[PDB]
Image (cartoon, rainbow, N blue to C red; front, side, top):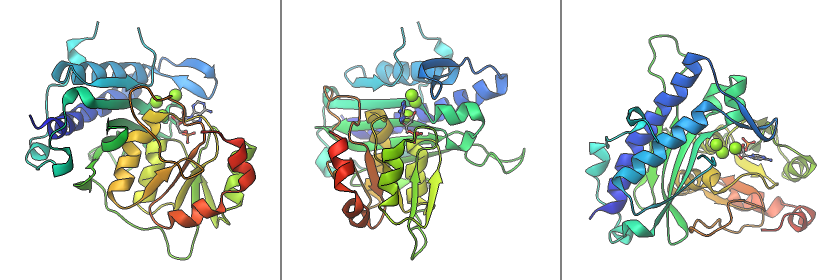
Length: 302
Ligand SMILES: Nc1ncnc2c1ncn2[C@@H]1O[C@H](COP(=O)(O)O)[C@@H](O)[C@H]1O
Ligand SMILES: [Mg+2]
Ligand SMILES: [Mg+2]
Ligand SMILES: [Mg+2]
């Protein structure tokens, strides 16, 4: 039945459609901003439309999946449906460990727009679209679309890119690069900081600290060598924030956990909140893990 690879190949095309929606909303000018729990907790027309497109498109082709999306939404336009699939991905053999997966056992975690606050600020390259695929509680495949990749290159440039990966195959669509030798460059939240977040970072002996939006964007920073660790000692992000990004990072030898070192779980019944934060690195994960203060750990219950 070739379920996993069929799913990944469709999710790739579905994520590309999502990128067209993200760009279309900016181009038409009205972001339809709704405030949820605070002025830094926003929902736009892009979040709502992309979620409708992704969920309807996946459910049309793979009705047995469990699909969980960030937005709590109440008839979808056929114009939002994506029926395509990547023929190239479909040509790749499924890793043998996943070859007998049944569709009803997959759980898909969707963040239709990740970095929404930064989207509304015009920090457009912070934005990603995240489609994460989990089996037996583990994140095993992921798609990350970055709709404004290349947007500063001029009117003749192609906009956007799609990064995808499967554990046992690899991760693709970017150039893997380690961060500069001899430096600790720690990346973290721009808009959702607090004292605990900054105290945990201080304990790492950073040479530089980057404050940017997006969980997907920060994993891209890790795999492209713009940062050496992603440290977020706080509640606030959810399973859809970490599912697809941890796959991409794990596929190239990195590691993402909570602040204690616990792996995150992705079964259908798990709580959405990542209540003990996020710690991630491409290389030297054990260094950063070793520097988390005990006081930070006692404050953050998984
Ligand atoms: N305190 C929070 N309230 C709502 N969303 C949050 C919070 N903290 C983190 N997030 C979300 O988690 C993801 C990563 O956070 P950030 O690094 O701030 O962009 C984004 O989708 C944020 O909107
Ligand atoms: Mg949100
Ligand atoms: Mg989102
Ligand atoms: Mg998010």
